[PDB]
Structure formats: C-alpha cells, structure tokens
Image (tube, coloured by chain):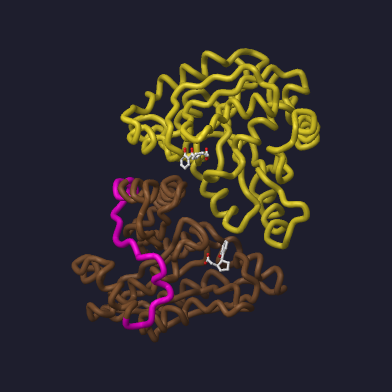
Chain colours: A yellow, B brown
Amino acid sequence: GGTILVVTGTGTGVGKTVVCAALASAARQAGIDVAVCKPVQTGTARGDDDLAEVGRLAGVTQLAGLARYPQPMAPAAAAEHAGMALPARDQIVRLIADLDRPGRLTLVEGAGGLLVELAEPGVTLRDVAVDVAAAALVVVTADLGTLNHTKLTLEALAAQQVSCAGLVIGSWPDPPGLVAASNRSALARIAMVRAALPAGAASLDAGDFAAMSAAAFDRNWVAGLVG
Amino acid sequence: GGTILVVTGTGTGVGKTVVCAALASAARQAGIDVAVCKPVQTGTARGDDDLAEVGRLAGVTQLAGLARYPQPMAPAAAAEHAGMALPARDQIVRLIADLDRPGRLTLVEGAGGLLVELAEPGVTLRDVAVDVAAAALVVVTADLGTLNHTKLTLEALAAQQVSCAGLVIGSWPDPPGLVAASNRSALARIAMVRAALPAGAASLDAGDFAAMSAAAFDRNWVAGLV
Ligand SMILES: O=C(O)C[C@@H]1CCC[C@H]1C(=O)c1ccccc1O
Ligand SMILES: O=C(O)C[C@@H]1CCC[C@H]1C(=O)c1ccccc1O
C-alpha cells in the first residue's frame, strides 16, 4: 500500500482539521496523491463537516466518511443521544484500507483527542493506527498546558508502539509571547515540530491556503512520507 | 508511616488547589491530621500562594514548600526566566517523607498537570509519587475533552504503578448541561468520582467552605484514607 497517517491532537479544538488540510495541500503540491477520511463526525446538526472543509481548503476530492452524528459531543455521547450505534473497529479499518494504495498519502482524521472512543468497546484512534500500521501526527497548541498534554499523548502512542510523525502547532500567534515562545522551544525539544500554522489559516482562500501550506511544511519531509 | 496522596490534575486551571483544600477540610472534620506539601509555586508576582489558600479555606497549619517563582508559567519556565534552578529531587522526596507520620494524611500538590517538570532534571510529580509510594488523586473538569485528558493521565499513572485514588471534578456547573452531565456519567465508568465541587467554591469563606467540603466527599471514604 501507500502511507497511512493518523492525524490526532492533544484534545479538541486544537486545529486537527486545518492541519489535515495543510498537510494534504502540501502533499498535493509535491505531486503526492492524497485521500482524507473521517471515521467519525459529530456536530452535523450545527454544520460540522471536516471532510467538506478539507476539500474546500486543500482541493482534496478523495474524501471518505463513515459514521455521522448530529450533536457536537464525543462520539459515544452523540451516538447515544441520537439512538444510534458507534461503528465497529473493523468498519473503520475497512474504510482506511479501501483508500490505501502505493504512492498515496491517506490521512485519517480523528475526533477530539487520541484516546477518544471511536468504536465499541473503548476502541480508539490509537488502536486503529496499530491495525493499519500507521504513524500519528499530533496537533498541539502553543498555550499554557500544552507540554503536559503533548507528553501524555506521545507516551500513550509509545505504549502501543505507534510511531510519532511529529507535532504541528495548529494556531501560532503573530507575534508570540513568553509562554508561546517557551513552549514551542520546549515542544521542539520533545519531538519534531513539522509545522506551525499561522493563526486564522482556516480563513485563507484556496490560493493563500496552498501558499501557506507549501511554506508551512518542509517540502523534503512531505516528499519523504511516501515513495 | 501515614497516608501520602499526590493531588494532580489533567492540566492547568482545573481546580487542583481548591480540591486539595476541600479534601484537607473534609479530612480535618473527620479528626484526621492533615499536612499539605506544595514543593514548587509559580505566579508569586501576582500573589499566587496555594499553600495560603489551603491554610485559609481548610485551617491546615502544616504547610510545606521549597521554592517560589514570580512568573505565572510552568516551573522550568519560571525558573529559566528568574535565572535560577528548580529544587533537586531529593529535596522534594525527603521533605515529603519527613512530613509523613502515622495517623496523618499528607497531600502533595504538584504544579499544572501530571508530567510537568517540578525538580532537576525533568523530575515530575509522577516520579515523586513513585519515590514516596503515594497514590494519586486526579482533578478533572466536566468540559468537552475531559475524558481523553483523564484517560491519558490515568494511563501515565498505571504505566509507573502509581495507584489512582479517584477523580474529583474541580468545578461542577449549575445547571449542568448536556455535555457536563454526559461527561460525569462517563468519568464514573473510568474511575470513582469522589466529589464534584460546586462552581465558585474557591471563593467561599472558611465556614461555608468546610460545610461544602464535608458534604462534597463521602464520609466513609475520607475516614478510611488513614
Ligand atoms: O474533533 C474535534 O475535536 C472537534 C469536534 C467538533 C464537535 C466536538 C468536537 C469533537 O468531536 C470531540 C470533542 C471532545 C471529545 C471527542 C470529540 O469527538
Ligand atoms: O497549577 C496551575 O496549573 C496554575 C498555575 C498558576 C500560574 C501557571 C499555572 C502553572 O503552574 C502551570 C501551567 C502550565 C504548566 C505547568 C504549570 O505548573
């Protein structure tokens, strides 16, 4: 197959989706075929659609969903509220394996943080990454609290031998402060900081987003993700 | 010895200090002798003194600290700004071991979350808990994202055989709301929820706080801590 990457984060609202669009845009501009999947989408009752947003920002057409729930909560609660079930583990693995192919980068976008339950019983994105032998890209903030959350996440990945593909700061303030500056320097000391997206990148139009995306990542690292 | 409990949380600003004071107060009202150790304090430029909050809210007098940095950052960053080092590992562990005595509940308050660096070099509250054979009480929020952060923290504890003494929700909203109510039920499936402190409790006077605290925790669980 090709390269499967799960895109996770230290928690909710850290920039997972915009980072997914940014890595997809960068990989597209390097000539890499990209597919993005979203095993579980909540918040559809308020218009949440991360796949649609990645298509808008990065131009990705190969977009695959599975489970969708209206309420903007964790999947187990949103499914329960709606009278619906979580998907099974093998259904998520099938969604991913159907997309995987040589020379393609398949990004698997999580819901919330790494240990969020996506399938019964207690099946998380970490288990899925083990199942499809994927590495994990971790989206982080630069805010107070971030190193503890980043270190807990990286420890949880290592516990199941899921490789860490690096960190991406989802929103980077221009200009930064003492805490943001100290955290980025300390984040870079615990793992590779692949990128740091400028604040408000999600508002950029397609052309500015593609320019930001290409500038945001090291063109050489993106190319090395998939032969 | 007695019983040593570290009081950690899933992050910063989750209610660690007010929970420390709530458990101290509940334990004092059950006739238990309570000491609180806060090895490292930051934010002293704006007046942060967590040991003083425990003193006033719960009446604890055995209040032990080692270092105080002016900047409201993590310890390592506040030390870096001040141009001085953090305490040494032995200082923290020996201070706690000296505090511990039979009949006593010694609560150890970290800074920020569980893997925050407290001592030299890169020593955490989790290491401290291993060294003094303490269990860990985990302060959590009810907000969106709390289950992930809770599971992350509890795995990191089990990974070093530090026992989990339960959760406390540092701030329980009124009225709850869908997400907060869903989160409390889910937290209870992860570990015992020992208390959920009413929102605003940090601002109560000492007599109102001791009332809230005595009702917040289960009598038998507190009485059995020592
Ligand atoms: O993916 C995100 O973090 C943003 C989404 C948008 C709607 C609520 C967030 C969500 O899904 C979520 C939040 C906490 C725990 C598990 C979750 O799945
Ligand atoms: O204890 C708290 O979380 C509140 C304090 C008050 C001033 C900054 C907070 C702090 O200490 C802190 C923040 C991030 C990481 C580690 C830390 O130790």
Left or right: where does residue B91 sit relative to residue A67? Answer: right
Q: Residue furthest left?
A: B220
Q: Nearer the viewer, residue A78 or A226?
A: A78
Choose between B41 and B3: the one closer to the eye.
B41
Magenta segment boundaries in residue numbering? B186-207
**Residue B190 colored in magenta in the image:** yes
Of the pair A177 and B101, the residue shown nearer to us: A177
Is residue B67 in sight in this rendering? Answer: yes
Q: Is residue A224 magenta?
A: no
Q: Is residue A107 above or below residue B132?
A: above
Q: In this image, B204 relative to A52: left or right?
A: left
Question: Residue A69 at what x, y percent from top left?
Answer: 42, 30
Residue pictured at 69% horizontal, 30% vertical = A23
Identify the residue shown where x is 59% and y is 78%: B68
Coordinates of residue B42 in the picture (x, y in percent): 59, 73
Q: Residue shown at 46%/33% (left/top)? A: A45
Q: Position of residue A70 (x, y in %)?
A: 43, 32
